[PDB]
Length: 168
Ligand SMILES: [Pr+3]
Ligand SMILES: [Zn+2]
Ligand SMILES: [Zn+2]
Ligand SMILES: [Zn+2]
Ligand SMILES: [Zn+2]
Ligand SMILES: [Zn+2]
Image 1 (spheres, rainbow, N blue to C red):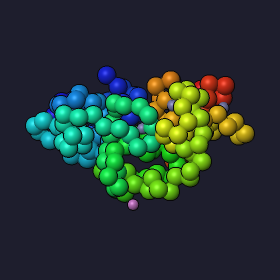
Image 2 (image 1 turned 180 degrees about the horizontal axis):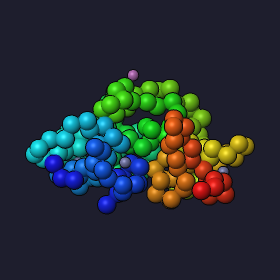
Image 3 (image 1 turned 90 degrees about the vertical axis):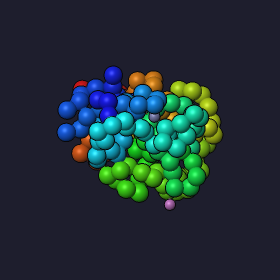
């Protein structure tokens, strides 16, 4: 395996929890952000390149492409980071961080919000600014690519619009 920031947490701090590179698509992920408890001595492939090596995939939860995908339990693909941040979604196995399931428990309202970053409605499940009584909505990956503050912390997962970026 080959051991640039982890595209799930956007942190470059490598260490016991290394950043792996897919030997086919050059995806870079922490073994703990993507669910890789054992690293192979030879080539490592992400789940997308194991299954759909010559075809990119769509996220079931956002309109954006690229980054780190797992299969869902219902015939789709989703971003790890989208599954992490949407409250009703989860991972069936929390060590392997797969499959992504419970997408059917997302309230229809999330698909009716308008992402204020890409301005699209109905193309993914939005989350909202964690600020009380701020209703600004965004896709998880749109918040990531736009550089909004997004923190997971022992586990609370708080994301903020640019008005409400918290002290730090
Ligand atoms: Pr299920
Ligand atoms: Zn990471
Ligand atoms: Zn790959
Ligand atoms: Zn996504
Ligand atoms: Zn968006
Ligand atoms: Zn806000």
